[PDB]
Amino acid sequence: DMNGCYSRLKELVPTLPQNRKVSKVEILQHVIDYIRDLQLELNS
Amino acid sequence: VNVLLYDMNGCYSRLKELVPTLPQNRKVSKVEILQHVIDYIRDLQLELNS
């Protein structure tokens, strides 16, 4: 469900804390930035 | 070279474009988008190091 996915994203993304609140938009912003960071880590 | 900030609508749009398993045209729910995002992050993480 939605809140399980958001919690998992906080666990997986190392720029987000886990147990203090973060806006869901700022969560997804960090997710986008982290996905780009990992894609670049592999390929130019 | 993107450092753009997105709102909620923009975030879900950008995630559909970033995540290769998400169709940019299909009628996917927000929870479905996040489920694909989670599995994709995990795959990327597993490809980083050994």
Image (cartoon, coloured by chain):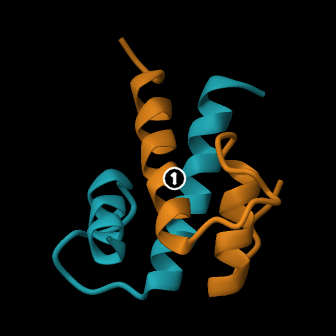
Chain colours: A cyan, B orange
Q: Tell me the chain of label 1.
A: B
Q: Position of residue A8 (x, y in %)?
A: 29, 60
Q: Secondary structure at mark 1?
A: helix
Q: Which residue in the structure is indicated by mark 1?
A: B37
| Residue for point 45% across, 74% down | A27
The residue type indicated by label 1 comes to Val
Q: Residue furthest top?
A: B50
Q: Position of residue A24 (x, y in %)?
A: 45, 83
Examine the image and state in which quarter residue A44 appears.
Answer: top right
Q: In what quadrant of the picture does the N terminus of chain A appear?
A: bottom left
Q: Is residue A21 left or right of residue B37?
A: left
Q: Position of residue B33 (x, y in %)?
A: 56, 61
| Residue for point 51% across, 66% down | A30
Q: Is residue B6 left or right of residue A9?
A: right
Neighbours of disc 1 within 10 Å: few (<14), some (14-19), many (20+): many
Q: Position of residue B35 (x, y in %)?
A: 45, 55
Q: Is residue A1 above or below residue B20?
A: below
